[PDB]
Image: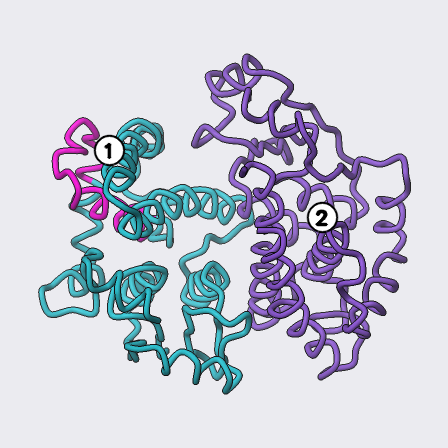
Chain colours: A purple, B cyan
Amino acid sequence: PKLYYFNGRGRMESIRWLLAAAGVEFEEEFLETREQYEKMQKDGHLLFGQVPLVEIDGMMLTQTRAILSYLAAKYNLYGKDLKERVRIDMYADGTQDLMMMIAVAPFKTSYDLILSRAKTRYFPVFEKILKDHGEAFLVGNQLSWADIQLLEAILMVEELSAPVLSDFPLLQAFKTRISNIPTIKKFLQPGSQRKPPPDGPYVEVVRIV
Amino acid sequence: PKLYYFNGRGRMESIRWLLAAAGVEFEEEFLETREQYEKMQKDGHLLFGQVPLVEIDGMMLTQTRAILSYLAAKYNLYGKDLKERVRIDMYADGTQDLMMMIAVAPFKTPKEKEESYDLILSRAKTRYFPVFEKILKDHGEAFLVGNQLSWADIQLLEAILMVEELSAPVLSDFPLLQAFKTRISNIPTIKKFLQPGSQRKPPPDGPYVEVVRIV
């Protein structure tokens, strides 16, 4: 893999996460300023003219959720059956939603709502999905790319309001046991590919391209 | 299947299309007003509390893109290999983008409305079509991915008509795509679904906006 995107989280972060959890080493190449983008464009790399771009298996993939489902299947993180995979995809969607609210929030002049939506909407669902089947994992007793989604979502909400999650026991226990999976652990250790929350001129590298 | 959603296009339209093209008969049940939604919610049907809802194979599937990929793979419209599938999925996402610009444009106020439509046109005429034109040119072929009807073809068509309704010319400058329209509109299942007494649903008007602001 060779990921192309900014030196920030955005739309790639969930991909880095999925790679990392797969135990797959990747290289990046940051879009710093304006000219870089216009070059990739006109060298025929960016399909519909927009990043992410992820060079992998000789192909230059380019639309976000497209790439996730290639990865998540290549490296066996989508279930066995369509019924398992649809549960994954469903979960993966909600989280995906939640995060993207956060990811886009810095560009405004919402956070208190994302909190209402996490505390009241998303977490309670995941909490009883874990409760109702007890199990260590979300779908079918195996590490699925949905678990990798939920965790990333948890810490992403946690970064805005750390308490947040106490009320959800099974989830606290989830966070622990999944953070302690070799690949996830290594990806969370201080000197990592993992990227920060959006700050200042992340927002303005991105407005300048 | 039993689709739940409004009596309008929105997020379900692309699902009805995919069902239709599969040669699969479906039943609907329209969300008319406020109370109906709050009932489905608290009877434990809506996972993260939001429609679409599509009852199928004994399961109550509920998040858009999650249902499309169940359908599109059950009824063999995703490729044979991951490399085909990802070409589908990549194409599926662009169209998906284009349409959802249109689908959400009615809920704005007027300057935004025009400024968005005229842009959707720029984006269709200058970004998405020219890409799909040469994908057809370069490989000549009748179909988008691997000489078979894939759910991407079903996506491109729906997108074409959807852009066409705003500005019918639009597409002259894309020969191969015109021909694309003709041949795919003439596939038995697509043909039937386009005949005037159909499940297919109209563009957003006023009312649709209103029912949807009132649930």
Q: In the rendering, at what x and y percent does residue B17 appear? A: 29, 61
What's under tag 1, amino acid-wise?
Asp
Q: CA distance from mark 2 to mark 1?
A: 38 Å
Front-most of B183 and B170?
A: B170
Asked if A172 appears above or below A182 in the picture, the reply is below
Asked if B102 appears above or below A88 in the picture, the reply is above
Mark 1, secondary structure of its residue: helix
Disc 1 sits on a residue from what chain?
A: B
Query: Which residue occupies the extreme bottom position in the image?
Result: B43
Which corner quadrant of the image does residue A122 belong to?
Answer: bottom right
Report the disc number at residue B118.
1
Disc 2 sits on a residue from what chain?
A: A
Q: Is residue B170 magenta?
A: yes
Q: Residues within 10 Å of mark 1 (few under 14, many from 20)?
A: some
Asked if A74 appears above or below A95 in the picture, the reply is above
Which residue is denoted by mark 2 in the rendering? A18
Q: In the rendering, at what x and y percent does residue A194 appear? A: 78, 39
Q: In the rendering, at what x and y percent does residue B107 appear? A: 30, 52
Span of residues in magenta: B153-179
Is there any visible trace of residue B57 in the rendered image? yes
Identify the main secondary structure in magenta.
Answer: helix
What's under tag 2, amino acid-wise?
Leu
Is there any visible trace of residue A1 in the rendered image? no
Front-most of B165 and B17?
A: B165
Query: Which residue occupies the extreme top position in the image?
Result: A35
Query: Which residue occupies the extreme left position in the image?
Result: B196
